Every structure is written in C-alpha cells, then in structure tokens.
Amino acid sequence: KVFGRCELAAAMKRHGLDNYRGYSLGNWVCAAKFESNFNTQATNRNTDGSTDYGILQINSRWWCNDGRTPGSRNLCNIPCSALLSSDITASVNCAKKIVSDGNGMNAWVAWRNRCKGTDVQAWIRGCRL
Ligand SMILES: [Cl-]
Ligand SMILES: [Cl-]
Ligand SMILES: [Cl-]
Ligand SMILES: [Cl-]
Ligand code: NA
C-alpha cells in the first residue's frame, strides 16, 4: 500500500506513534517519506546482506526474521514479511522497540540525514487529526 501523507499521519497516530519517546508525529511521517516513500511494500538490501522492510525500512540484522541474514536477531519477534502489510501495526510496534533502543530516531539513517532538525511539522500540516 502506498499511503498518502495525511493518511499515514492518521494511521500512525491511531497506533500511538504520535509523541512516542518524545518524537512528534511529523518526525515519523518524515522518516517514512524518505525511508519508503510511504510504500509499505518497500524492501532494500544492505551491503552486509541484511534487508530493510516496510514503511520504516526496519532491518533484518536486528529486528525481524527473514531467514537469510546470518547471525541476525529478531528482536521484534516477527517475520520481516509482516512489515510489508497494508496494515502498519507490525511496523509501528517494531518501530516503538527500535526508538526505545537508546539512540532514538537516529536508528533511521534517512531520519538523521533528512528529517532531524528540519521543520518536521510541515509533514502533518493540513491533516485532519
Ligand atoms: Cl510534528
Ligand atoms: Cl536469518
Ligand atoms: Cl494501518
Ligand atoms: Cl531521544
Ligand atoms: Na534477523
């Protein structure tokens, strides 16, 4: 599923991401924009052989099981395929674990390089929330 900007903002809010660990909704929408272009089916292979999955590009090295990332963990206790669903519940629940991990949203390279410090409120502007 390719979400619209405000549509994703509303889904993220309903799943409790708004202000989770102090990160306003705009941060999460901005991260999803640059990680996946709002596409739940996005996948990208990393140089180390792991793969990033879904709207927030969660990596199989630590967070989900894809059966082909040797030595990796599955800290969200999910198949990586669950991160590709039109329903964002699995990605949100896993993202909540990641952002509590210690480095906050810096775990998302696209957020650090393209959202951090910017006017992230723009990403929810005009949305009926
Ligand atoms: Cl915001
Ligand atoms: Cl594996
Ligand atoms: Cl959803
Ligand atoms: Cl933080
Ligand atoms: Na894994």
Image (cartoon, rainbow, N blue to C red):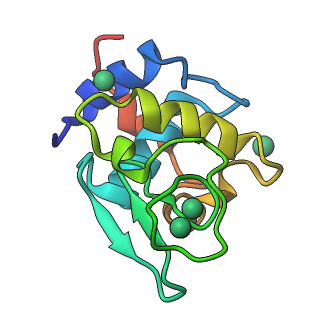
Q: Which residue is at the far bottom?
A: 47
Which x, y percent locates residue 109?
56, 67
Which x, y percent locates residue 11?
35, 21
Give the vertical position of 39 relative to 26 (above or below). Answer: below
In the picture, measured across the screen, residue 120 lies left or right of residue 102, that is: left
In the picture, measured across the screen, residue 102 lies left or right of residue 1, that is: right
Q: Quadrant of residue 23?
A: top right
Which x, y percent locates residue 101?
78, 47
Give the vertical position of 106 relative to 82 (above or below). Answer: below
User: Can you say which quadrant of the picture contains the N terminus?
Assistant: top left
| Of the pair 18 and 93, the residue shown nearer to us | 93
In the picture, measured across the screen, residue 106 lies left or right of residue 124, that is: right
Give the tally of numbered discs. 0
Q: Which residue is at the far right?
A: 102
| Of the pair 27 and 105, the residue shown nearer to us | 105
Residue displayed at 50% across by 75% down = 50
Residue displayed at 46% across by 65% down = 67
| Of the pair 38 and 116, the residue shown nearer to us | 38
In the picture, measured across the screen, residue 2 lies left or right of residue 75, that is: left
Residue displayed at 42% across by 52% down = 80
Which x, y percent locates residue 118?
54, 52
User: Can you say which quadrant of the picture contains the C terminus?
Assistant: top left
Residue displayed at 26% across by 27% down = 6
